[PDB]
Picture 1: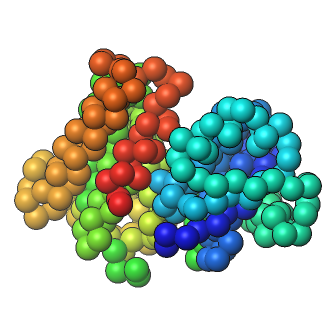
Picture 2: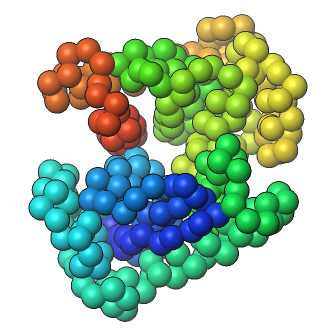
Length: 143
Length: 143
């Protein structure tokens, strides 16, 4: 739709190392999730994530995040303005701007663990298998 | 929907080198496009592409391709059977199974060129900028 409001954060998932930082977006009205893998939490990683999320879900009206450096930076402020997307920040875990994405963090990590163990991976997923496993987890949660 | 029929092919786009092989899927009923970048045309690259496409569009009922090696291989036949997705092959360019995806190849390449030149890239896109540019092209065509 034309009035989406997203919540975005980062969560660490060592099953996906070396690119173990998962950037996670939930669309607040639909609950759809987009997830991407990153080697580090940086302003540019957030921006790469949102570029992917726009290609999957469409362009949102606003994004809610916490007040960490990758969200409060001049870089990210300009990227969001470039796209015409509004942005509000708050404290880590604030229920208003972040509780839904915290729940998606946990749903994703549980699903990644179940799929991985099912394929016989009890610890880190082999690098060559990670992309398809992450995409299967996203498919499964969105169904 | 639950009855999608896709057409998939590969097209070479040197603006995106070194990962210049674009895997392209169109959903035949909706005309939505998914595109991913690959360094080589292989059975596994097709499979990585379709894993992404399932996370974006949902699981299709069938996929139409040509009869190249990456589509007729025992590997790809098993991957598709694993997912419960039916598959038909035909001759390169057959209008029945491939004309729509050939049109998406051309729409994508034109859009990539327009965006790239707009950002001042007259030849290859800088590697660090390619992911977001490809995702912008996919967004723009699907809108």
